[PDB]
Amino acid sequence: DEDQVVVNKAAVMVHQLSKKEASRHAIMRSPQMVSAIVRTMQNTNDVETARCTAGTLHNLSHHREGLLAIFKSGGIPALVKMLGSPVDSVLFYAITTLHNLLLHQEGAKMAVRLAGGLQKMVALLNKTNVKFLAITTDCLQILAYGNQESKLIILASGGPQALVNIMRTYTYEKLLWTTSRVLKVLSVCSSNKPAIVEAGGMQALGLHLTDPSQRLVQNCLWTLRNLSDAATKQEGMEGLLGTLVQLLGSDDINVVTCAAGILSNLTCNNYKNKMMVCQVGGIEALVRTVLRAGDREDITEPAICALRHLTSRHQEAEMAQNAVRLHYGLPVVVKLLHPPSHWPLIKATVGLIRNLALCPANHAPLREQGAIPRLVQLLVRAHQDTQREGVRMEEIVEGCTGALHILARDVHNRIVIRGLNTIPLFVQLLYSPIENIQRVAAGVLCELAQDKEAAEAIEAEGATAPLTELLHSRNEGVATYAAAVLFRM
Image (cartoon, rainbow, N blue to C red; front, side, top):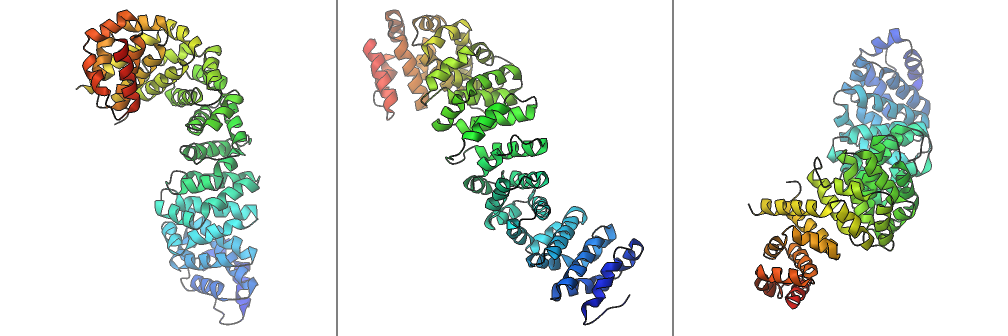
């Protein structure tokens, strides 16, 4: 084998040779002709030489030694350079060769990044050949995974919008999956996440939640869960929400887990989403989910959180509060206050009960199921733990006190609450440094004080003094409750 200086036609044979595997290892061992093969490719304007050269580099990318040749011959910047070509044949050869290097060649990742490979691959995402896009997106996945720097470059190059458009356009499974994996990798980056959401990533990913490919569905769910928390106010979420509710019935536990977590995130302080989730039967579905989950807290916790969002501050909140009871939900909710539940689940369950108790028809069943003494034990113990990371016991204090504040609207609950000797504790909570604890403490005292016997007990406990002080609280809610107890005393 020799080297041809000017006319292209040297390349139409070395390529035509490059198939004979016996010869390849000659080509593979000449740190002068690989270099020549490369040099020509980057420099010619003979489109056939371009594809003959690139095609040759491809064929060699199939061997451990073949990669090394191209690598230490500085082929990577050349290949990246070739990603700006019009010829679809050379585009395909270059990206495939890069793909093999990215997969098997030690040190290829860094060389591609250095060469401007990220920006060029992102720019190629507006192509229309699905096989080409599948390769290109997989390269991006390999480069971005566990490399925050690459993630930020993909974002700056317009990565998010381009990938989302792909998810909205194509049906080719391998491409949808490979693209979804890039999105998943980007979805944990604090900068990429809002951009993906901004590009309509959540609605786009939602399109594929009924696809028969489980790896595609699962990747879309993982990405959605990362994106969903603290998204902006998106519209066009109707379909996504309805599908998530359906997925709760799935036999796959990871589908059920993700669907619950996304619903929890999407309903948090979004009354439109709460309405829509309730309207497609979200309450019944979440209750059933909690029942089936048993003690798997990675399911119950977000499902309960979702239920808590769905039972407050939207048009059909009252209906949701009844609906939890009507679908046999009350006993299991109370049960989740007990071991083996961990703190995050207990905190969420207390908040749900607080909401359920806003519905008078839940007052008796919550009492009968034993919610009150368990809430009181949780409160007593949590207060002591404060008086001496994860979940803070102050949040359990405030939560339990708040649930009891609402339950105390019922005359029989007030009797049970008082009978558990809670008044001294409630009065002591008036001295809390936390305004929100002062408020619910003063609030529950206010409910109890409507019964003369309790009012005297509250007075006897020395409540006049801290209450009188709370009259001057910069927190108006605290001051207003404090005045009402003082009155009734």
